Image: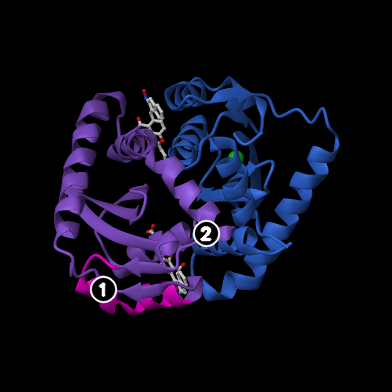
Chain colours: A purple, B blue
Amino acid sequence: SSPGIWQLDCTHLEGKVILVAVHVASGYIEAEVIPAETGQETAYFLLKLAGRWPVKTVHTDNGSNFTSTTVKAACWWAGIKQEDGIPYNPQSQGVIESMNKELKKIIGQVRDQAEHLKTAVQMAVFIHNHKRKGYSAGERIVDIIATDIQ
Amino acid sequence: SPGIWQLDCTHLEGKVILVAVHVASGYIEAEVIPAETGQETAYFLLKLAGRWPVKTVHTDNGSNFTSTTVKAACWWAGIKQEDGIPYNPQSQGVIESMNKELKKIIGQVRDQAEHLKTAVQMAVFIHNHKRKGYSAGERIVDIIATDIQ
Ligand SMILES: O=C(O)CC[C@H]1COc2c(ccc(/C=C3/C(=N/O)Cc4ccccc43)c2C(=O)O)O1
Ligand SMILES: O=C(O)CC[C@H]1COc2c(ccc(/C=C3/C(=N/O)Cc4ccccc43)c2C(=O)O)O1
Ligand SMILES: [Cl-]
């Protein structure tokens, strides 16, 4: 059920890890900088996400997070169906790849305005979600979910 | 009114919980911080505005209203920074009641989480999903979707 489907994505910059959740149907994202991708960090990130949006299903970004007892506990707690992230549809890889490149580009364009990477990442989230493509990802996610509620 | 948020700072376990409330829906986001500085508040607002269409923020106190860092974040994110003076006196009691409710939920989950920040995010989840019959999460999406359309 596509209003509730999210995909996890982990990318790297400046020796740090950027964890991204993408609302598949809209392209809307949330993201955080973490020192390393652990089960505990991923679990906490998912808890935050699911408190903020109606997360029904998460396609996990790798097998370690899929396997993680802590991630499984968070998904249980928050009522999330934890699934694999195998791109049975091969265009999924390229879409995530393209978004990571886009995000890193935006981070570069703002990096000087922020002392810390985490600030630049949140600026990138803002720019990404507001970008008009003509609706924005932020507009699309609200519309999709509102239509589902109705 | 679809774009109006209110900041709220409350305390528990010698730590600070910073809350943003979407006034029309009662929907919240929250974080635990060591202390409420301009820098922490600024970063919190940047996060919020990247996630929801934040037009106006009623700041929680005069220090954050005055803060150059908070003003910079509001400028960056296109947020109108306003005071949080309750010209409508029922605003105080509503925020008061929510802080009490949140602390209650935190108590009900505190044992399930080692760290306060986890308990706070559990509380955010429970608050936003609670049916009152629609939930705050349902109301915010409906309000904003109607505004877009
Ligand atoms: O560094 C960061 O940002 C996050 C680091 C840690 C913060 O603390 C935690 C964390 C990750 C997990 C936990 C534990 C959970 C449970 N244990 O049963 C049940 C549960 C249900 C849902 C979510 C988390 C937990 C904790 C915690 O124990 O509080 O992420
Ligand atoms: O501890 C935590 O979680 C948050 C602490 C810090 C994280 O870093 C920061 C922070 C708060 C502020 C900044 C600086 C900003 C600017 N300077 O011009 C312009 C700007 C525009 C918008 C938002 C932040 C900033 C930084 C930073 O410089 O990166 O919050
Ligand atoms: Cl304080």
For residue B17, say whether it is visible: no
Give coordinates of residue A27: x percent, y percent.
33, 48
Residue displayed at 57% across by 23% down: B80
Q: Which residues are magenta?
A: A60-76
Please state if A124 lies on the left or on the right of B127 as rendered.
left
Kindly report which numbered mark, 2 or 1, lies closer to the viewer in this rendering: 2
What chain does mark 2 sit on?
A
Give coordinates of residue A77: x percent, y percent.
49, 74
Q: Is residue B103 above or below residue B142?
A: below
Quarter, ligand 1: bottom left
Q: Is residue B67 above or below residue A6?
A: above
Can you name the residue that lies furthest to the right here? B89
Give coordinates of residue A98: x percent, y percent.
17, 46
Disc 2 residue type (three-letter): Asp
In depth, the one of B129 and B37 nearer the eye is: B129
* Cα gap from disc 2 to disc 1, whole angstroms: 24 Å
Residue displayed at 45% across by 63% down: A55
Q: Badge 2 local density, few (<14 within 10 Å), some, or many (20+)?
A: few
- The residue that label 2 is drawn on is A148
- The residue that label 1 is drawn on is A84
What chain does mark 1 sit on?
A
Describe the element under mark 2 as helix, strand or loop. Answer: helix
In depth, the one of B146 and A55 nearer the eye is: B146
